[PDB]
Length: 132
Figure (cartoon, helix red, strand yellow):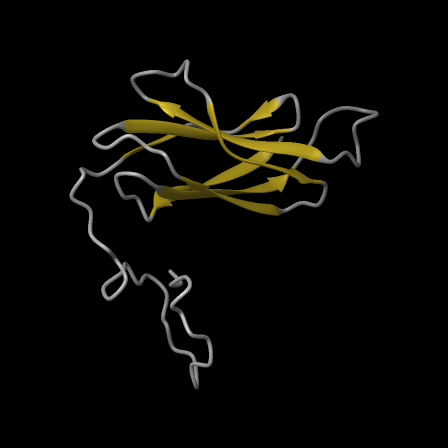
């Protein structure tokens, strides 16, 4: 089967969110083996699934393929749904997330540190982007 793992939506604010997934293994049919599959990770409003917006559109020919999408232009207090569309024929499972209100936090001094930030001698100056 086409195995597409979906990573839970994180870094969610009112206007943006970081979503991702991993296309572990791809299948299609004869003739389409070794094809650069267009990964379009689509998101829409839970209230309006007609507004199919593209979070990210990239091409993958190598699997497992880890893809991520940074969504901006989100509506506050709004529930959204997302899926990874791989090639012209496949879609993943459906996840849903909800944005925040117009009172969001900066999330830089205190961020959700799920991994350990233990790096012997921190050479990287994270003033451009803070790692999760």
